[PDB]
Image (cartoon, rainbow, N blue to C red; front, side, top):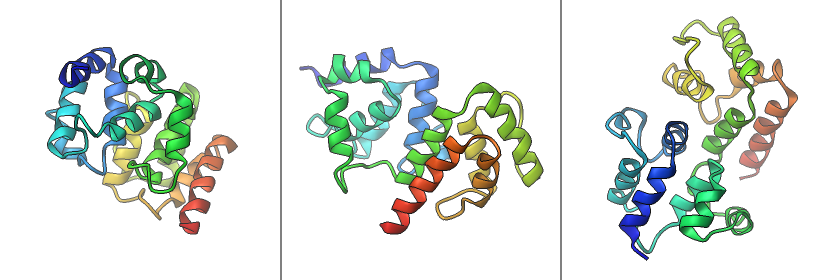
Length: 185
């Protein structure tokens, strides 16, 4: 069990989409403007090592990240970890290290189709003029922009709900389920 080699091996299997997803899911530990020099997954893992979030004896955050981005394949191959274990662990109060808010936004981005993404842009433009949007941006990029313009955040979900309600009930459900548990605390 060579820890450094394993991190490299995992990183080699992660693609550009995975990197962007992992960066998003790491936002409340590695701020948005500090992610620029992070060019591959191993560099992300090394930043997490520097922050003592990832160590030979501390794999929980790496496992949580890989689970949330649905790389169950890499969890099996490189970390001998099953979906069943992760569901049990992350359902235990206090175990998850990614905020429920950040997971909620990521889960919206997983659910949204290509056509729904076009609708999101169009509907957001009706609700807001502060965001700089373009057709190349994915939904995570849109969320980052909404956060930059302070129209999205924890406890600032009005615009997100107004847009999602017009796209698909499935999205509003994700938000409402998150809100209910959050207020429950």
